[PDB]
Amino acid sequence: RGSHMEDFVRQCFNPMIVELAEKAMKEYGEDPKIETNKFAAICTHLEVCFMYSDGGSKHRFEIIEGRDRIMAWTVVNSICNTTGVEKPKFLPDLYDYKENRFIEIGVTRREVHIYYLEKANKIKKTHIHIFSFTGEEMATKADYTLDEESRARIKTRLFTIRQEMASRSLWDSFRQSE
Ligand SMILES: O=C(NCCOc1ccccc1)c1nc([C@@H]2CCCN2C(=O)CSc2ccccc2Cl)[nH]c(=O)c1O
Ligand SMILES: [Cl-]
Ligand SMILES: [Mn+2]
Ligand SMILES: [Mn+2]
């Protein structure tokens, strides 16, 4: 039972992202063949996390997302036990060695302010950075970590993804799936 959305995800995202996404959902008991919008959302978030860590200097970011849950907590333990930063209650996506804070990266198909609130209500010290499929962004204390060009090409890619699904009539299903 193979959807259009699943075939589009495999042709739209690079194979390392797709496989990390697949491992992730299976690890949490989800099927990329069925929960195809989530499949698409996971790849998107993953690609945004990787572009984001690429925007800094060489050694600036540790990448927490995309790892096995046990190994992700292992690295945050090490980060915490060497920088003296409080251990987050939930797994974040990155750690910033320059600013010494964990980052939760968000990608939403709804309005900037709500997901941040939803995200901030659940987080309760880590930095939050939200990106939209429309090109809006919001970060904690209005501190956006990266320079403008790095975030700009993230927004550019999100909108390209938007168009590629719209041209395949899959955008409507994806927007109202969140
Ligand atoms: O790391 C995360 N979860 C760890 C576990 O995730 C899986 C992995 C596979 C299957 C089920 C959960 C994480 N999760 C969330 C949302 C809200 C909290 C649970 N959640 C989700 O299940 C939505 S899947 C999602 C959707 C859009 C963007 C990104 C993602 Cl991951 N959003 C994030 O930005 C994020 O990093
Ligand atoms: Cl930098
Ligand atoms: Mn994450
Ligand atoms: Mn995230």
Image (spheres, rainbow, N blue to C red):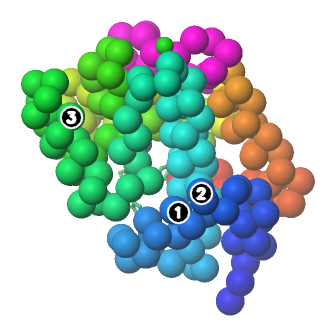
Image spot of residue 108 (x, y percent)? 54, 40
- Is 154 displayed left or right of 160 in the figure? left
The one of 8 and 170 positioned closer to us in this rendering? 8
Magenta segment: does it hold 153? no
Q: Amino acid at mark 3?
A: Ile
| Farthest front residue in view | 58
**Residue 116 in sight here:** no
Q: Given the image, on which type of amino acid does mark 2 rest?
A: Ile
Q: In this view of the protein, which residue sits in the foreground, 106 or 173?
A: 106
Q: Compared with residue 52, is residue 177 higher up or lower down, i.e. above or below?
A: below
Quarter of the image where one finds residue 121: top left
Looking at numbered disc 1 in the image, what kind of residue is underneath it? Ala
Q: Residue at x 28, y 23 (%)?
A: 101
- Whether residue 138 is in magenta: the answer is yes
Please tell me whether residue 30 is drawn above or below residue 146 in the rendered image.
Answer: below
Question: Dot 2, crowdedness within 10 Å: few (<14), some or many (≥20)?
Answer: some
Give the CA distance from mark 2 to mark 1.
6 Å
Q: Could you tell me residue 38's position as x and y percent? A: 54, 62
Please name the residue shown 70% across and 56% down the image. 13
Percent position of residue 128, x then y: 37, 27
* Disc assigned to residue 79: 3
Q: Specify start and end residues of the magenta stretch as a single range.
A: 136-151
Helix, strand or loop status at disc 1 = helix
Residue 58 seen from this side? yes
